[PDB]
């Protein structure tokens, strides 16, 4: 009579569901679970802080449509991971945070258990669902629920709570195997109303000035070929939002990225593809035509009419809706007016000339534009990389300047504009893909997760961290207004040498003050596949404060 | 007609209430508030992550009984600070986290505002109270509430939400000044039932084997002289809990710290002073006498009978209760039986001899005992320092070995056993006191807040960080059980040189492999008052795993 | 320039969205809103308690797919309505509860406002969404969101909070009109993956013992003709769950209702149509074959694998799914094994014979069977009624014995087994339909909403309330086990005459003790269309417990 326990059961359930990586920080009561998972051939990546583990998991979910798995301990570790779970739900990235919890009887009486918290209830506001498993025979179905919840609808974080007692709880091994559930097709296709599709095509065909906006839902869908075919067939100008850059290459002739304001102000019919009318699009209000008509492809009927009335909702999974839209277009072809494309190009060209001046003009110290021009030159020759990016000036300028050539290669601060995603996203992207990562980091941004450089060294991951060191938050030229000479609230240490941090962990560091030095250091870093920090000296006065 | 705005009003309210320090991370919508606070002579300390800002604030509250102030931005920064606010409430440390929030109208409709979150409601589970201020004329009374709530009863975290619009909202300056509220005596004395006090003394006087346990409520109360007088008058053996070490010096002849198990198993009457029967005391169950009778001094009547029935509750603020207890003892003196003290001393001596062997026996590599013996030798000569401590082996062994000579000088992982409090507590303690800090840090523990070494350098704070580098969580000799040769879930990088991190920020680093080297490096670090990291090479096999 | 205010704007928005009835209880700050809605041609129905108003709104939603509107005041009224909102969400019935709230500034500071509560946050755990409107120009979009959310996915309750200030807030009339949103097609069709449809048909065609279960979702969908055609085409036995009775008439040859236990114990393939594997189906565990394979038609992907692994999820709206299932069956026809249908029929006849004996045997006093047989005699002759039903014995027996002939005519205690839905569901059904209602009520059940008989009288609604008066909860023969002779916890007043309650409100009352009296009284009630109570004297010892 062979016995097993809850810990072995949950590991087997993860294995059967093709989980091959767990991102976490161990401790009571989950250390043995991690060790056993690794024994069973799951890759374990241990972090310096759970929030970076959670960011890594969500990145892996965005890239793959399989929920990333984040493992934490009870209360103190759980709360750190929860901050990341919250971010995944806001952004629409599938992940499951699995946390140990303490003694249900003691916690339910608030008697002061070890790491006491009702973690299930704590996670509820920040997750698509929060489940807690009390019986080992329910672990398999619980994981099945968590997987389906995380990837169905608009994807997001799910919390799965494993009390210490369920991990230790025993059952007969043969019976235990019958309770494990392998989920086939956890996010089934949901097809739109055919009438919606016909109405959408008809409205586009009548448009004088149609515009498609590709949002991160579009990128997540992996409908890359359908989106490109639709756009090129009808020659419809498009605006890629940050993490949608690269679905079509950013150099594509139909991209209106360089005339964004003109496009939003003048488009008459706008087709949102997995793009919400939230603050990133000014809620469809400021800067938009008074009477824009919207077509909206979104999986969530609850998102329709959230901000502006939507003329033609196309509710369904984006891949299925794009298949329908393409089929309807084939039967009822149209071509966007050439005049609209031509006038867009006038505006794009005006801005391109202004950008080109900034990119190509040398300054000492460096500014954002000439530094990022050097980065742009290198990355153009290394189109296999993933790009992670966070900061304020460092974020907005890199978003504009660094062209993405392939889809789902850009990961950034996202909908909540979180500083602290940089190292976790780099680790998640590198582990998931096996590809090199370049992280373009504000100096303040980097400080939120910088201890993870040891994690990067520990697993010898090919991450090149390029820190835009302007000596502060937005700018480094702040002054203490009291006259006391203290650092201002936005100042960081003058001339910190972040490259030297790598010396602690046997990584590589470069300090750079010119575009030639930056180009060399970045090329060498990427080619070397060694963990590398490049400290870029940026003019403290170059940035603007939002 | 001179006008002012909400931002100026809240700064003036903080000033009038003797807030002289704010710990935070700025960004929209609070940067100008921080700059203006600093203009007005409030010291601003900016962190690399809000959780360390929040830990600093709570430390300052524990040391002073004045709530520490933590300032954050909206959603992403707020959530990071919230993790620390939660910790303050659990531990009983007064603090106020002030966060900017976004547009109430947009957030209430869930339309996707910039940094959208109902932060007030989010903070409610983790705070004594959560307030949100919509009108500038209510800022003064709101701050008054927050101060009184944070320090009254059992102290804890309070959340104060300032929507961006209230900061910008204007009012006439003279009228505005009339709405500012200076709180006098925000935590008034609450005196116990005199019958409780008489019953407590009577029970102690009948005890064969009485024991006092001093908890962090005792330390917080600053009733140092009354506690010492009571203990010495009746010669009552006492057990200091971690953050109560030093109320009486740890070398005091009545301390039963070195016979803890014997004391708990054999005491007949136990007087808890600001000490909960939670997991840290095994809930008064395992390891206790079957029929212990409890006296409990606590400010919270809701804590009485939480775990074991309490024979004599003494409900009131600990300082007031100790004044009553001392007065009642003076009228009805007794002396603890000498036999009980003598048999305690037998057991203390048995353990002292075992400890002394471990402390004084050289090993290569170093172990926890001989390394901490070197630390003990230095700290005995530097009794003006604050000691911050976190880890597992690093925590438990330092707690046992490093004697505290003065009260409220030890700050550690606390009731939730949080890793990540080390740098924030060191910064809070240093800024508050103007004294040197020694942080004795596990290598895993340090990784949770290690980027704050730049903060320490930026403000040139006299913090010596001693990292017990055993190469992992508990131990550094883990193995990948799959045979693939990957780092085990508990391993960190082999032979990381954390001392080299200081090179980035112009701090000082020492690497040490012997007790002589450690003693020298630690003495020099403390005397120098320079930001310093000491990397201590500890045997990877020395630690135990809980 | 002509002005308007929030109150006028929201009424106009309700009108434009074809809201023609509001169910409510007035008071500050919503009385004028109700007066004006009524002025504008909306039918106002005022209740004696908000819980019944909310039940009425949810009933109307179930019957129509248009959310019922419940209107309440702030805290005390809001909380009463919330209990009903919670029930709507659990059951999947669309409704919007609109509540006034107090002063956001005062409530956010917890200063003790008039009827102070954060109502939006209070409603969140019980609603699909909770929205709060601060600006009158956002009232139209807020209502548009509330409508869409309430009827999409699995339908449910939405809370819409209107602070007193928004109702009073003014704007220019013409501009205000441009902010009103008329929602077209609030729940668009969502079609299932074609492969899942083909898989479902394939599995059914291979089944030896297939069974369809029709749940409330099937009833709500209004796919009556598609369901009938599918069932009849393949001759698939079906089980109607309570509120799905009548989709096909309960006397249909293929109904397995009279062999329910045998059918669940023996089916090999079970097709759930808008039916959860919750407690009502014993979670697919107790009473089921060990290896049942499930097809599940549900709109909510989060419901799949909640309890038992589901072999063939068919995710999409039920009407759309059934259209696809029907089309696929046509291309791939099959006939359910005759042997299976025959065996079911053997079991059905045996239970029908046992039923007939209980039904046809007269007793004094009446029992549940002969009383309900009398009721069925009358309802057989009066088929255009609505049936409301609640109780324990009164519920289970009426569910079994009263055949439904048409869909969406039965309303009962539902998924949470709530006592107190009877009067509200009766009012909602009669107001919505214009048809007579028969409410078959346990005497305890009736007590939960009994004051609403005045409401029934006030609006002269054709409701006949048939109270099964057995003198208590389950039974009326309880004894005080102390010997003191007090009523037992399940006893109600011996021989209460509920019919006399109607005297207070000029309604009609009958007391009945025999089947003949019962038949006459019920026939007269229905045909008179007068508010009527029939007090039915039931044997206190007839019922069973639990
Ligand atoms: O700030 P957001 O509102 O997010 O706009 P975003 O960062 O996309 O673009 C900012 C500006 O840079 C312009 N633009 C963006 N990327 C590029 C580029 N690579 N080259 C030239 N112009 C650019 C945009 O058109 C916009 O200018 P506009 O207001 O004149 O249209
Ligand atoms: O682990 P906890 O239950 O928290 O106990 P704590 O860390 O206070 O003490 C652990 C052990 O070290 C002993 N002790 C604590 N500090 C010292 C010290 N400085 N010297 C010798 N013994 C010590 C305690 O008595 C206890 O041993 P015991 O079980 O034999 O009493
Ligand atoms: O109790 P539930 O599990 O809810 O079952 P339900 O109320 O539908 O039926 C209870 C019993 O009455 C039987 N049944 C239900 N309605 C009728 C009816 N009108 N005539 C005869 N038998 C009936 C069921 O088959 C079941 O008996 P079974 O266990 O022998 O199959
Ligand atoms: C967790 C978190 N805390 C605070 C903020 C506020 N914030 C916005 S940008 C920013 C950093 C800006 O400085 P940096 O990253 O150095 O970029 P720069 O503009 O200097 O290039 C911060 C802290 C945030 N977005 N997230
Ligand atoms: C925020 C948080 N995450 C995880 C844990 C679990 N945990 C307990 S001790 C510990 C670290 C132990 O290693 P270390 O600090 O290096 O001390 P050592 O025992 O090796 O001396 C961790 C991560 C925790 N307590 N808090
Ligand atoms: C709001 C609410 N309170 C309590 C219950 C528990 N409960 C179940 S059935 C029932 C009443 C049973 O008696 P009755 O309605 O008279 O029917 P009978 O069995 O006597 O025919 C009650 C109170 C409930 N379901 N809902
Ligand atoms: Mg910067
Ligand atoms: Mg360690
Ligand atoms: Mg009854």
Image (cartoon, coloured by chain):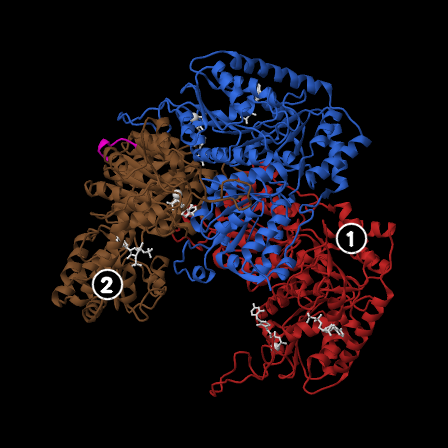
Chain colours: A blue, B brown, C red
Q: Nearer the viewer, residue B250 or B34?
A: B250
Residues packed near mark 2 inside 10 Å, few (<14), some (14 to 19) or many (20 plus): many
In this orientation, does residue C117 appear?
Answer: yes
Mark 2–mark 1 CB contact (< 8 Å): no
Is A25 left or right of A182, judged from the image as shown? Answer: left
In this orientation, does residue B138 appear?
Answer: no
Is B507 left or right of C436, judged from the image as shown? Answer: left
The C terminus of chain A, quarter of image? top left
Q: Position of residue A11 (x, y in %)?
A: 57, 51
Q: Position of residue B28 (x, y in %)?
A: 43, 33
Provide the chain ID for the residue under circle 1.
C
**Quarter residue A340 falls in:** top right
Q: CA distance from mark 2 to mark 1?
A: 72 Å
The N terminus of chain A, quarter of image? bottom right
Secondary structure state at the residue bearing disc 2: strand
Quickly name the residue at label 1: C200
Q: Give above or below for B263 relative to B55.
A: below
**Residue at 64% over, 73% down:** C441
Q: Position of residue C268 (x, y in %)?
A: 76, 62
Residues packed near mark 1 inside 10 Å, few (<14), some (14 to 19) or many (20 plus): many
Q: Nearer the viewer, residue B501 or C402?
A: B501
Say which of marks 2 and 1 sits in front. 2
Numbered marks: total: 2
Q: Position of residue C55 (x, y in %)?
A: 61, 61
Q: Report the magenta residues as a range.
A: B526-531
Please say whether residue C32 is one of the residues in the magenta stretch.
Answer: no
Provide the chain ID for the residue under circle 2.
B
Q: Give above or below for B397 relative to B229.
A: above
Quickly name the residue at label 2: B211
Please say whether residue B529 is one of the residues in the magenta stretch.
Answer: yes
């Amino acid at each position: 009579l062979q016995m097993t326990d809850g810990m072995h059961i949950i590991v087997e359930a993860l294995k059967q569901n093709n989980i091959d990586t767990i991102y976490g920080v161990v401790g009571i009561p989950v250390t043995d679970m991690a060790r056993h998972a690794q024994a069973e051939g799951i890759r374990y990546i241990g972090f310096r802080h759970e929030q970076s583990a959670g960011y890594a998991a969500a990145a892996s979910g965005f890239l793959t449509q399989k929920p990333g798995i984040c493992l934490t301990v009870s209360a103190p570790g759980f709360l750190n991971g929860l901050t990341a779970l919250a971010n995944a739900t806001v952004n629409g990235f599938p992940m499951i945070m699995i946390s140990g919890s303490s003694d249900r009887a003691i916690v339910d009486l608030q008697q002061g258990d070890y790491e006491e918290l009702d973690q299930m209830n704590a996670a509820k506001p920040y997750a698509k669902a929060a489940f807690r498993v009390n019986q080992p025979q329910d672990l398999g179905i619980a994981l099945a629920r968590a997987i389906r919840v995380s990837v169905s609808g608009r994807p997001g974080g799910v919390y799965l709570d494993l009390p210490a007692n369920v991990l230790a709880a025993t059952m007969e091994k043969d019976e235990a195997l019958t309770t494990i559930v392998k989920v086939e097709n956890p996010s089934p296709a949901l097809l739109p109303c055919p009438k919606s599709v016909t109405s959408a095509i008809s409205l586009l065909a009548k448009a004088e000035r149609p515009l498609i906006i590709l949002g991160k839902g579009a990128a997540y869908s992996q409908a890359d070929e359908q989106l490109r075919e639709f756009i090129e067939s009808a020659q419809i100008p498009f605006l890629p939002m940050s993490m949608a850059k690269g679905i079509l290459e950013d150099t594509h002739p139909l991209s209106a990225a360089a005339a964004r304001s003109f496009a939003l102000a003048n488009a008459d019919v706008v087709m949102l593809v997995g793009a919400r009318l939230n603050w990133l699009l000014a809620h469809g209000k400021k800067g938009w035509a008074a009477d824009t008509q919207f077509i909206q492809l979104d999986i969530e009927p609850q998102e329709i009419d959230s901000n502006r009335p939507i003329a033609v909702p196309v509710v369904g999974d984006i891949a299925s809706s794009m298949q329908g839209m393409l089929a309807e277009l084939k039967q009822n072809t149209f071509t966007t007016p050439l005049v609209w494309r031509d006038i867009l190009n006038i505006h794009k060209q005006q801005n391109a000339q202004k950008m080109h001046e900034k990119l190509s003009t040398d300054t000492q110290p460096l500014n954002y534009f000439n530094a990022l021009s050097a980065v742009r030159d290198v990355l153009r020759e290394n189109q296999d990389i993933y790009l992670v990016n966070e900061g304020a000036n460092t974020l907005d300028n890199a978003r504009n300047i660094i062209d993405m050539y392939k889809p789902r290669r850009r990961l950034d601060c996202g909908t909540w504009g979180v500083m602290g995603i940089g190292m976790g996203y780099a680790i998640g992207a590198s582990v998931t893909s096996g590809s090199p990562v370049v992280a373009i980091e504000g100096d303040s941004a980097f400080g939120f997760s910088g201890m993870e450089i040891e994690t990067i060294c520990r697993y010898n991951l090919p991450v090149t961290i390029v820190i835009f060191n302007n000596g502060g938050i937005y700018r480094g030229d702040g002054v203490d207004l009291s006259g006391a000479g203290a650092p201002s609230p936005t100042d960081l240490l003058h001339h910190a040498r972040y490259d030297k941090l790598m010396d602690a962990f046997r990584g590589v560091g470069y300090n750079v003050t010119t575009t030639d030095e930056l180009r060399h250091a970045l090329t060498t870093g990427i080619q070397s596949r060694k963990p590398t920090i490049i400290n870029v000296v940026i003019d403290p006065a170059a940035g603007t404060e939002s």
